[PDB]
Length: 443
Image (cartoon, rainbow, N blue to C red):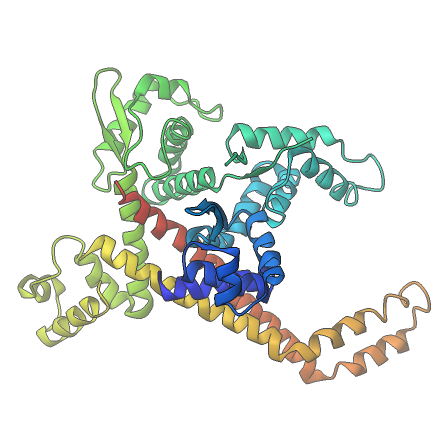
């Protein structure tokens, strides 16, 4: 499935909605397609509790329902859809980035309330932005709506189909398109230079509609029209563009390759090749993570030919025999070369690490429950103090409640909450990559 995939799903639902949604969700994954009744029977849970759980499931766009064989309304969960709940913040913040905070909010609710019509969102946010606005001026519904439309135009927002409305949702596919796009652009930017990567961005910008998020290669595009779709910040010449192009295609890395020429040369982007190299580098950093620079350097030499045999291993190693033997074992030991294979393996290892993360976060607030509220009251004492009876001695009394270790633990826990939160994000990006390669290898 895998096991960690399931476990992860569970934790997800638990955090967002409750034990009800989790139990049933878990069951919908575990037993595939099932009517309301068989779910309420195998779970040992009533039908109203079942019905409540399904509400938060579908409304939020995750569970599917279809009328099977004997006209029975059967229900089903979709694993990938559950896991997308992870990228959710990054999806959000990138939106904040691109179409301001106005955008930030639009998306913010479209996931957390799931299915919502155009209007509902528009006003929801306008008021949710009038509360932030300096007392007055108000948020004109229009700007809100513009950004919304702009989202539906760039396909970052699309409609809820059919089996003052009606419903709209988040097109995390065009998000995958953009993350794919960015990961790529930046890879050029670090493996080549800024100008090159800007060309890429130009290519992807005209390959954001005519091509897919899982296509191995884009659509052919001539030097001339690319030179035409040039950004305004770049006043770069044709011949410049030409030496650049020839360089890009004929690059040992090869994330781009020529298709015709023709005039002024037909050119393609190698999505497959690009993804594989991305994953490869990730692997390099992992080898350097647990088996260090020593084994990472040797790993980098495994990129030319091999696994199997050692004749050329110890030779290209530049170290004694016994050493080359040991490290050769360690790399094939946890299956490190088989590209896709190690990729999928790694993927599971990700899911595992995540389980750990949530576990520790969950438990830290769990066992430190009797400290959470103690802090809350403390704050609710300066609520009616900074303004009414600004009493400094009262503030000291507040300080004497929270003895040294309790607050040092609040800091300890808070910092640990962070170590987790950060690691979490990191893994997310990593997962997007892996899965995107996995789907890319689906040609």
